[PDB]
Amino acid sequence: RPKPLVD
Amino acid sequence: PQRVSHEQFRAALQLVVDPGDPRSYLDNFIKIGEGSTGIVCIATVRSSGKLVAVKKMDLRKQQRRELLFNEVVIMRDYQHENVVEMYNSYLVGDELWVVMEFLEGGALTDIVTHTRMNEEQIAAVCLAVLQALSVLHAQGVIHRDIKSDSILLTHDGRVKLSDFGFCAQVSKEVPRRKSLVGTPYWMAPELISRLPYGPEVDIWSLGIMVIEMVDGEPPYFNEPPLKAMKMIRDNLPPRLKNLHKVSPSLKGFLDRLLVRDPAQRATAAELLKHPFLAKAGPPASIVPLMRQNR
Ligand SMILES: Nc1ncnc2c1ncn2[C@@H]1O[C@H](COP(=O)(O)OP(=O)(O)NP(=O)(O)O)[C@@H](O)[C@H]1O
């Protein structure tokens, strides 16, 4: 499952 | 500095959470899953024997450290039948431990990837999410990570929103947010374009989850996250695979979610009145979809 993106 | 920033943050959290160590009343800490911020365990209440979930998150291993306040605050302030119950929060070493209810039904992803949901079941999930979002949006709180992974189930088929770690708040003074936060495939086009955005980004993300429930995957899921984002940015709103089998109330519903202009996109409070949600089945109708029953 794809992982979230921050910044 | 790294030390000054960390120690100060740990001390702030220490005041925010409950004092003590949960191991003083919990046994059998066993890992059951991992996410972005940390891992998830089950544990046993020594006296009763009842199971709970414990989310452990390392303070040193976060991209934006300050987002860990959400992991505690949101479940405190927003108790709701469609929101995961939090019992206690603790600081153990350099980790934040959040003690919450164990959702034995698992994540919606497990269902969506394996079987196909009927409209009755889809409406039940949508209603549950929107009821949770309406309470959050009313207070200016945006979830920012709406996806099937963030949706959990009980054994009796009830549906709850989870994973509040990425929440931001807007108010009269702070109208919109600017941070790039969320999961690439579920991200709203205005958020990807790095424009000021509000709670409307959750509404779009929900539409992507609807595509999940119908088709099994978000649009451009085979593409790399970075490449797929530019596709959501430039292209027109994504459509369902084949509309021949979907009801007009579902089409109409999805048409209010997947609008490029956030101002034309429907709010949570508006969608709660949409005719499609009247088809929502009982919790019992969700049960056959789960792992044990497949
Ligand atoms: N209360 C719970 N009961 C059962 N399973 C859970 C519970 N909370 C999380 N999980 C699962 O355990 C795994 C841990 O991942 P997750 O909790 O999503 O980490 P995360 O991505 O950092 N969440 P967040 O940063 O707050 O958006 C996921 O696969 C969840 O589906």
Image (tube, coloured by chain):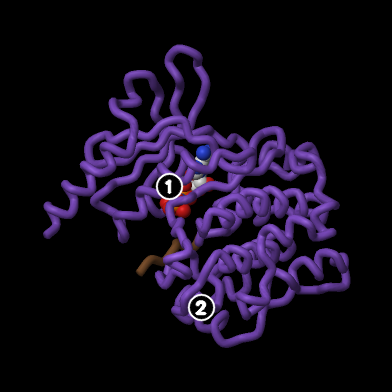
Chain colours: A brown, B purple
The CB of the residue at mark 2 lies under 8 Å from ligand 1 = no
The residue depicted at 60 percent of the width and 65 percent of the height is B205
State which quadrant residue B92 falls in: top left
Q: Is residue B193 above or below residue B198?
A: below
Residue at the extreme front of the image, as rendered: B172
Read off the residue under disc 1.
B34
Q: Is residue B105 above or below residue B68?
A: above
The residue depicted at 80 percent of the width and 40 percent of the height is B282
Read off the residue under disc 2.
B229
Q: Is residue B154 above or below residue B50?
A: below
Relative image position of residue B28 (x, y in whole percent) = 40, 24
The CB of the residue at mark 1 lies under 8 Å from ligand 1 = yes
Relative image position of residue B7 (x, y in whole percent) = 16, 47
Residue at the extreme top of the image, as rendered: B47
Tell which tag, 1 or 2, sits nearer the viewer. 2
Quarter of the image that includes the N terminus of chain B: bottom left
Given the image, on which type of amino acid does mark 1 rest? Glu
Tell which subunit mark 2 falls on. Answer: B
The span from disc 1 to disc 2 (Cα, nearest Å) is: 25 Å
Is residue B263 or residue B21 the one in the foreground?
A: B263
